[PDB]
Image (cartoon, rainbow over all chains, first blue to last red; front, top):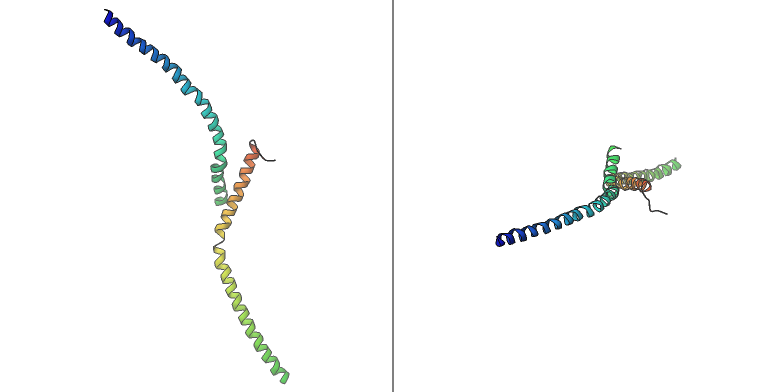
Length: 65
Length: 68
């Protein structure tokens, strides 16, 4: 059947195309920022500790001393 | 005798100045004692920023410091 052929063929073509888009987009979208995120965040720990963690340090130091 | 009368009178004005002096000093110490209470808070905050600067300096020196 040519109508059934057209239906399943076009529909599965769309699915295959969308899945190729899925693979590429998902991989880049979730890979590229991830490294940048964790790098900036380990540095963020190194920075935020110098405002907040030191605040806890000074507080403990004074209250205990 | 007359010398003694003169001496007693000078001593009287002396003693009056003594009492006035010391009463003012009582007010002085009382004032400072009341003030003192309004200083420990500031002292705590001073030492807080002090140790803040000390610890952050030690940590900055540990990491890539950006001083001279």
